[PDB]
Image 1 (cartoon, rainbow, N blue to C red):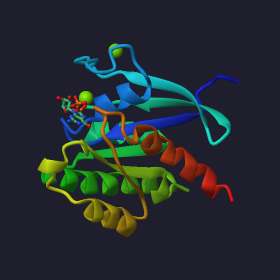
Image 2: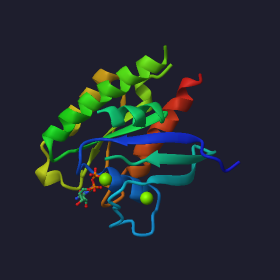
Image 3: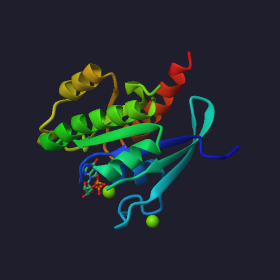
Length: 171
Ligand SMILES: Nc1nc2c(ncn2[C@@H]2O[C@H](COP(=O)(O)OP(=O)(O)O)[C@@H](O)[C@H]2O)c(=O)[nH]1
Ligand SMILES: [Mg+2]
Ligand SMILES: [Mg+2]
């Protein structure tokens, strides 16, 4: 009891909100500003749908990305809804995840990934639409959640989504 139950990796281009999301989720003491030059691994003890869970989240920032993928079970791929280039990278990153997980499996499934459209509080400046993010995720077989690390909006839903999916798979 109390041990790490799930290993999640953050992926996404710089500036999309990876660190901010993780610090928000884990209720870190300087929730608004904590951002060390060298990324940390973060922990959240929680109860997800009645089951006590302990998430270990790898914050990150090609070959090194492959190590991050081998050493984690679930994935949160973040893009910035105000930056279409970040959305394009996220799609590329999803393919890296699948291909890498395919290598090891010889199983991993796209539902163990969630695409996160962050900075949704910046609605008046979005370059990527909600329906567009939703349709990409549907095309790929993965989750899609819109979040605001700044306001905390939908942050838990985003992270817990991949745990929920993993459990859904067992039956
Ligand atoms: N308005 C807004 N700004 C955000 C949000 N998430 C992150 N930021 C800002 O985006 C910048 C980069 O955030 P950071 O967490 O360091 O991104 P990272 O490089 O992916 O880890 C910082 O100035 C954050 O304050 C959000 O949800 N809304
Ligand atoms: Mg960061
Ligand atoms: Mg550290």
